[PDB]
Image (cartoon, rainbow over all chains, first blue to last red):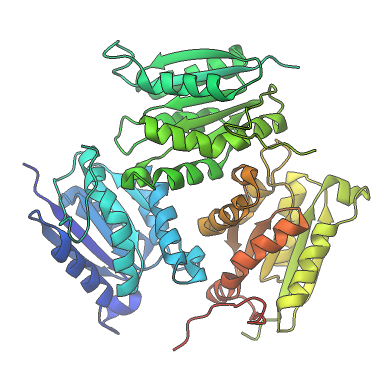
Length: 175
Length: 175
Length: 177
């Protein structure tokens, strides 16, 4: 009867300093509340882009809070301080190249700079971790593209049961 | 001129028990016999989801049976026991990112969960190894997508000569 | 950026380096650069045999000593064992950019079925972006038209020199306030 807990991690020095409002994390939470039919809790965190803090935070959410899914936003570009993908790979046992490929494909429809994104996704135990973009609009387009495969992925790793509203996002399951 | 030997490996803890016939393996064999017009033999193996055994099987086929191409099916998903990609990476000295990229791309057209596939391809000596999915529909779109480049790839690594029926799938080759 | 823009063009070809073939690939890249860039820049041109150590040494020299902000290589990206340009590139970079190889193979497949045999990639070493291009002059332009729009901005982000392109030829996208 595993309970569904979804982690939302905003990685931004500015946001963590309070220099500006976290519209990215808000965009992710709003999206989840809007499309998920099944019951679920949220573990929200806003941290600066410190490599060690990112890894420690991902591990805490998966291991200690029992998250079945963790969505990050921020730190996925070419800049040297953007280490979210590095942190993600460092805490996962298996990576899923298909996520990064599709997210870049979808973004490319908007801007050619989509090829500069290093967003990825991987598995840590019964938890799926996915790197999302920063802009609320791009976050929506991104989730509409990958969410259809997320619930089933979590099923396959032993995570909590999640289902979405087919009228908004169809969670494909080989039935 | 090396003799053309093609390995077909079905990876499943179930199929290695006789729990059912091997539809996936048969689909691959039938495809090969249907499109290839040059002389070739098939080395068929059905093994469990054990990384070490998969590694040893691929090495046996490449090194001892002299396979120039090895096609695997099964164990490419997110589940922890799906270790075919890891075993493939372990025995190859050079990976080809283009294969997993295109295969997931064509598979995604009907299967949203295609982004959960960790299929890849690599080279071990003069043998090309390619990970295929388990479902027939996916196996077909994947082979139709990559086969046009397989014979030529084999030429470049010094493997045996293989050609296909252009009315089914044309194998590229320079003048 | 007050940085002086220096672009490296490295041809990795045993035959080109020995004087067997004319390097139409390197020439194609240089002509493309001069054709679309609307800002001042110098070119560090090198032609070398496909020796992994030399490839790594050359990339490192152009980035660390010549101060290149961009290095475009041509050759050695296929499945044959001697093609080790991607390996050398990953060896000298600290951060890879999967989107480059992905897009380049995607736009190439529309014309070359064996595009999936290409192992071209791109990565970052300090404030220098390194991108692997194909050998055929025709394929070089196709790959560049696809990825060049993202190159100047990527260089901005890593602290490299300022480069801009003629919007009528290639539009270098950059976010504006």
